[PDB]
Image (cartoon, coloured by chain):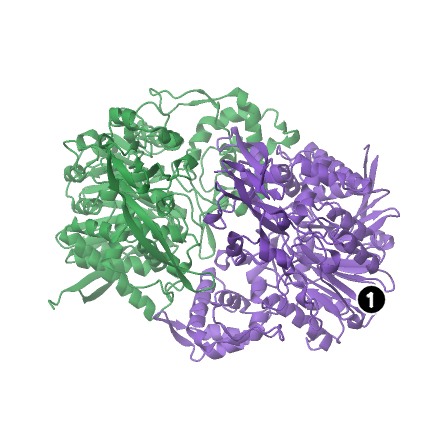
Chain colours: A green, B purple
Amino acid sequence: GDGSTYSAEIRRTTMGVPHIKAGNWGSAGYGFGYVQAQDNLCTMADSFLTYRGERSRHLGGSAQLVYNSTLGRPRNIDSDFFHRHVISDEAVDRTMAAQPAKLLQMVEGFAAGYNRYVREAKAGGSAHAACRSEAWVQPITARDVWRRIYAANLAGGYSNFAEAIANAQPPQSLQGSNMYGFGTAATGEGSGVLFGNPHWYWKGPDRFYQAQLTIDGEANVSGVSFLGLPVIQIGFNDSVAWSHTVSTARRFGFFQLSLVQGEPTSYLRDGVPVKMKPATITVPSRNADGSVSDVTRTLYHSEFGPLVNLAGLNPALAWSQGTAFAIRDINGENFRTLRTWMRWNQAKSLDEFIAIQKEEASIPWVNTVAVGRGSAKAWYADIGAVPNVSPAQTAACTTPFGMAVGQALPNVPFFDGSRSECDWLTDADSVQKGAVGVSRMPSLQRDDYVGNMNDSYWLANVHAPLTGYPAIFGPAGTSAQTLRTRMGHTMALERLAGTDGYAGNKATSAVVREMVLGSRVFSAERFKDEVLDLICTPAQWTVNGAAVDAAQACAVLAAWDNRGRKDSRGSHLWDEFWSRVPTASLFTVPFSAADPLNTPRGINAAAADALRQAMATAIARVGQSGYALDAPRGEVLYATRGGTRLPLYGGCGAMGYFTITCSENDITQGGYSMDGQPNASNSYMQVVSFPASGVQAHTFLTFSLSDDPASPHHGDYTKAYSAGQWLRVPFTEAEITGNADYRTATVKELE
Amino acid sequence: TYSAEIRRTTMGVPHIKAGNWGSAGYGFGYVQAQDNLCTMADSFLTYRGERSRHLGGSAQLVYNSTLGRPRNIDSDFFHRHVISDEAVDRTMAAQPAKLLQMVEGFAAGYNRYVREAKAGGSAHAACRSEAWVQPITARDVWRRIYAANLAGGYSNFAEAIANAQPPSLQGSNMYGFGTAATGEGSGVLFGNPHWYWKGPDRFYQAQLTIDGEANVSGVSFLGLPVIQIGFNDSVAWSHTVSTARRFGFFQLSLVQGEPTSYLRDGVPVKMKPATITVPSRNADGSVSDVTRTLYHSEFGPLVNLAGLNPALAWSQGTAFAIRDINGENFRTLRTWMRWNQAKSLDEFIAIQKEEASIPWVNTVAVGRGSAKAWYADIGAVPNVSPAQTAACTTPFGMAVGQALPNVPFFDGSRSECDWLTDADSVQKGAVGVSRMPSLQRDDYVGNMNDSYWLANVHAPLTGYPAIFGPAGTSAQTLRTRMGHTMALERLAGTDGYAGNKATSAVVREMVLGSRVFSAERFKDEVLDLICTPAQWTVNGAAVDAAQACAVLAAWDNRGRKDSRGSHLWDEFWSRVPTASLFTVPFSAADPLNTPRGINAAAADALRQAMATAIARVGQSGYALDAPRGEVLYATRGGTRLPLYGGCGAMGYFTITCSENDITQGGYSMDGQPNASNSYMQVVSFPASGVQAHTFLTFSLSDDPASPHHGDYTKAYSAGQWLRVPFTEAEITGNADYRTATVKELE
C-alpha cells in the first residue's frame, strides 16, 4: 500500500458556502463530494438510482421520477431502461478512456467523499432525516459519477426522448437563462463585468451547488456545479468569469432506417444489410405489494445511435416491417465537456479561455459569455458540439416521413439513413466527426456588451448583428425575438444610455446588481396602455352575454407601473390576463429586423372582444385564488422557509420579465408558491468584476445550499434573495478566514 | 307556467314545494345551479362532448367523478359516441310523462339561474362570465342522467372506447337496524356513501314536496332531479358500491380483409360507424377540428384493450367490444322516483324487484312499522350461466380472468354466448329477480363494499351467481371487518356507548367513532416485535425509534381530532409489505377475525416501514405525536377545521381519506379527496313521523362566496349532526327559515 490519502480542508463561510482546499485533484474531489452529500444527500442518493437505472427496484416501476430535471419525469421503469441502454458500461468505458488522469482522480475522490458522508449519515444524527435510513442511501462508485457526468451531456438530445428510446421495439423543451458580458467601454473601468443568470431547477439533481475549489498550485475557482458534478460549470477565477444560457442550436437529428425484408432488426446501408446491435436488459421492479419482479426488454442501437419509438409523435412513424427510426445526439460521442470546464477553471486569461473553447469545441447545449481580467472586450460564443449538415443535404436527404414532425421540430435533420451521403459531415476544422467545424460556429467580441437570453446568436449585440452561420444555430434576422430577449437588450441599451433610472451610464458591478433584479415586465411596459385604452372605457362590459364590472381591474392596472416587485399591486392580474390573450392577429406592426427590440407591436383594435374575454377570465381566476386584484406581488409570489412566506419579485419570461421567478403552481392553488418544483427560475446568480484589489463576485443561490429542512443552510440564502441582499462571496484566503461565519474542518482517509 | 316555492333552512337546505312534477323539477334545477353553477356548467360540457372547444383537447377533466380524469378530447369522443342522439331518444322514449315533465322543468330552472348569474351579482364569480356558462336543454339533462348509469362499465373505459380503431369504483357503508336492534317501534337506517367532495357526481341535499304525489328528502348527484339516497314519511334507504360486475367483453372474429366487420355463426356483420368531429381549442387560442370514426357492435361499443394487454390490440383477425348492461337500462330514474313516493318498505321492495334497475349499488332500507330491515343487490346485472362461461370464455378471456374475475369475456362470434334471459328477467340479457341476493333481518343488515355474502354475519348468503362477487373464498376488507365488528359490539353493549340498542342517538355517535381496525388488531403485536430494543439498525443506519414506539403505545387506536400519533400509524401501515404478513389465514368460519397474527419473520420489514413512516412525518413538519385534527382538516373561510376519521385501507369505518401526501401540508381535504364521508343520514320513524339527522360534509355550495360553502363543514368538524326539518311545521318553524317563489311561463 502506497499510503496515499485524501485530505481536504473544508472552510465554510456565510450561507454555508464551502471553500475546499486540497493539495491535489483527488483530494479536491474528495472534499467537494463530501460537502455536496453533507448538504444534499437525499436529492443525490435518489439521483444515483436514476443514472444506474435502479429506481424501479426501490421505488416501483410505475412511479414517476421524484424530481424534475433535464430528463423530465418519466416512469421509473422507462427511466431505468433508458439509462441502462444509453449509459451502458461501454459508454462509461468510452467516456473514462478520454479523460486526463487528474480528472479520473478527482472523480475517484468525489465518490470516496460522497461515501464518507454516507457513512456519517448512516451512523447517526438528525441531518437528512427524510432519507438516511433508506436502502438507496448507499455508497457509489467512480463509474456512477461518470454515469451522472455523461447524463448531463445528453440534455439537448437523448434525455428528451428517454421514454421513446426505452420503448423502441421491432414489430416482432430545454429553455431559459440570461447573461451579459460588459466590456471596459461599458463599465468605464479597468475590467469588464460578467452577469451570470441561469434559469434552472430549484430542486432535484440538476440543481446548482455553490463552492470554491483551491487546488494548490493548479486552480482556484468558485461558482456552481450541478449536484454530482466535480468541476465548476458557471463561475470565475482570479482571471476570468463566464456563464451559460441555453442555445437554440439543435444537438440531435433522426435517421430513418430502411429495414431488411423478413428481418426488422436489420437496415440497409447503400444496399447492404447491417444488423442493429441488440441489448437484452433486465430491470428489477418493486411491486405495489412489496415483492420484486424482473422486467426484460431487448432494445437496440444503430450505427447512428439508439432506436427510438416515434409513434407518439405520429402513429405513421411506428417501427414496422419496412421502416424504423434512430436518434443521434452529437453529445453521445462527446467525451470532452468535463475537461473543458476543468481547463476553464484553471484559465489565466480570456484569451486562454477562448483558445480552450475553440480547441475542445465541446460545449454541449449552451451559449457561453466571458469577461477576463485586463481584456477590454467581452466574449460571446455558441462554440460547442453541433450536428453538421449542409443545405444540399437538407434538400436531398429529408424524407417524406420527416414532414410529420417538420412543424414540431424545425431545423432538426431527419435524414435517409440508407444513404451514406446523408451521414453528418466533417469539416477540416471539425474537432469531432459529424460536428460543425470551429470556424463555422458563431462568436463575437465587443468592448460595450454581449448578451443572450435564449434566442439565437443573431443579436449577441444589437449594434452588430451576427449572420451567415449554419442554419442549425437558429434564425439570423428573420424571426422576432422573445419578449425576454427584447427586455434583456432593452435593459442593456438603456443602462449605457443612462435612461433606465439607475446611477450614471456605466454597467458597474453595483448598478448591474440592481438592474438585473428590477423586474420590469415587457408585455405591460409596451402593451398595457394600449390594451386599457382599447377596453376600459366603458369599464362596464358584456362578455359572453354576462355583465362584467371591470372598473376595479381597469383602475388597478392603470395605477400599476409595469413591474413585478415585492410591493407592486395588481401585477398578478396582468400575468393571468396576458397569458390568456390569443396571439393570432394580435399585433398590427410586424417584426422588422431593423427594429428587433420594438417589433412586433401595435395592439389590433379588432382584438377588443377577445381582450375583454381574457381580462374577464383573469379577474375570475384572481377572485377564485382569494387574492385581491391589487394584492402586492410579494404576497402572491413567495418561498416558504422556517414557516415564513418570504416575499419574492420577478416573474415568467412569457410575460417579458428578465428577472425570472416562475412558479408552476396555479394562482387558484395558493398563489405563485416557489415551494414545489418551479419552472426554470433565477438560481445561481453572479455579478463578477476584476477591480484593482482582485476578482470580486456577488452571488445568490436563490433556493439555498441544502435540500434538508433541518439544515441552517436550507433557507438562509433564500431570505437574503427575498431581501435583495447580494452575497459578497469570500475568495482570497484572507477573505475566507476573515469571514464573520468562518469555520474550518479537515476530512481525510486512505485512498 | 312553472311555479316552485323554495324554502331554505339551516345550512341552506332547500325544500322545494310545487303543485306538479314539472314545477318541482324547475325549483330543483334552480337551487342546484344557484349553489353549484360552476361545477354544473363545467359538467354539461362533459356530457355534451364540448369540453375541448372551450378548454383545449389536451387538458384533463377539471373534476374527478365516475369518469375519472381523461383528456378532454377523449372524454368528448366517448360522450358523443356512447351517449349518442339515439341513446338519448331511446332513454326518453321509455320515460313516464311526469319525469319527462320534471326534466324539462329542471332544464328551465337551471336556465333561469343562468340568466340571473349572467345579469349581475358576485355569486359564482369564478365562472359567471365564461362562454360555457350557458343555457341547456332537457336532452342535455337526459345525457347527464344516462351518464350516471354507466359508472360500472362504460365510464371506466371512456378513453379505451374513444380510441378503438381498426389497424376502481369503490366505497361506502350502510346499516339497516330492525326493531329487535333498536328496542323501539321502528328500525334505524344509517346511510354513508363515500363519495366525491367536488365535481358533478357530488351530492346535493334537498327536499321535494309535490302536491299529493311525493314528499321526499335526501340527496341527488348534481344534475339529477330525483332523490337517490334519502327518505320519506314511510321508508328510508341508502346505497353502497356493489361488487357485482355490470359489463363484459365480446371478443370479435373479424371478417377477412374487413377489419370493421365480424362473424356471427359464420355470417359477416358490419360494425356500425359514427364519423365524429370535435372542435378543440389550441394553446394559442385558435380552435381546430379533430375527427375519428368510431364503431358499435350489436353488443355495444368497440373498445381498445391494448392497454390492458398489448396482445389484445384490434388486429386483422380480432377485435373487442364492451357491453354494459346499463347501456340498455332506461329504468333507473323511474325507480328512484317510485321509491321517492313509496308508502311502505313492502312497496319499496316490490318496486326494486319490478324494476330490477339499480345499476351498480347495493340497497339497504328500513320502513315505518316494519320489524325487519332490508338488504339487496337486486338491480341490472349481466346474466351468463356456468355452462356458458365454461363454453364461451375465449383463450384471451381466460388470461384476463386473473385480473378481472367474473367479468364474462366471451366468444361474440357464437350466438349461444349472448347473455341469457330468465323467465323473471325484467331486461334481456340480465339476471332474473329470483336469482339476485337479498335478506331481511330484525337485528341488522350492513354492507361496506364487500359482496352480498355477509349482509348479516349470523346468516350469510351463499349460492348466488358468480358475477355478484366471491362469497366465502376471499377475505373481507379491514373496513368490512370493522363495520360488522361495530354492529355486533353495539348489540352486545361492548363498544362503550349507552345501552345495547342501535337507537338513532347512539348510531349517530358510533358511526363517527373513528376506530382503526388495523391498529386495534395488530399494533400491539407490531410493537412487541419491533420496539424492544427501540434503537435499531435499518439498512445499515442507526434509527432511534424510541419516540415512535412510545407515541404509538400511548395512542388508543382511534383517529379522533385529539388523537396523538394516529398519522404515524397511517404512514406506517400503508407501507407494510403484505406478502406473508399474517400467520393465521383467512377462514370463512371466522371472517371478522382472520387473517391475523403478525409474522415474526416480518420484523426487519416492519422496522423498514416504521423508519420510513418516521421519516415521512418528519419531512411533513408535524410532530410524531401531533393531534390528528391538525394533520387532517378542511379549510373554510381561511380556518383549518379539524377533522377525524381516515382511510379504509387502515380499517377506518369513519372515512375522511385525503389524496394529499402528508409531506405536502398534511392530510388536507381541500383538493379532490378520495371517496369520503359526504351525505350521511341516520333516519328512524318514531310516533311523531320520520326523523332524520344529516351531514353534507363539504357543504351545499361550491362557491367560496356562498354562506353555504363552509357552514355544514364547520358542523361536521364539531360532530354536530343536523336535525333536518321535514314536516311543513318543522320547515316554517326553523330558526333559519326563508322562502322565495320562482315562476315563469313554460
Residue at 66% over, 42% down: B40
Which kind of residue does numbered mark 1 sit on?
Ser
Subunit bearing disc 1:
B
Q: Quadrant of the C terminus of chain A?
A: bottom left
Residue sitting at the far right: B212
Name the foreground residue: B379 vs A204.
Answer: B379
> Left or right of B241: which side holds B164?
left
Residue sitting at the far left: A2
Image coordinates for residue A676, horizontal then vertical, percent: 44, 50
> Left or right of A151: which side holds A673?
right
Residue sitting at the far front: B266
Name the foreground residue: A69 vs B622.
Answer: A69
Total tally of numbered discs in the picture: 1
What SS does tag 1 mark? loop
Instruction: Give above or below for B126 relative to A389.
Output: below
Name the foreground residue: A166 vs B246.
Answer: B246
Image coordinates for residue A607, horizontal then vertical, percent: 53, 23
Instruction: Give above or below for A569 relative to A143.
Output: above
Classify 10 Å Cα crowding around label 1: few (below 14), some (14-19), many (20 and above): many
Instruction: Give above or below for B3 relative to A719.
Output: above
Image coordinates for residue B260, horizontal then vertical, percent: 54, 37
Q: Quadrant of the N terminus of chain A?
A: bottom left
Image coordinates for residue B524, horizontal then vertical, percent: 53, 77
- The residue labelled by disc 1 is B186
Q: Is residue A148 visible?
A: yes
Residue at 50% over, 26% down: A529
> Left or right of B340: which side holds A516?
left
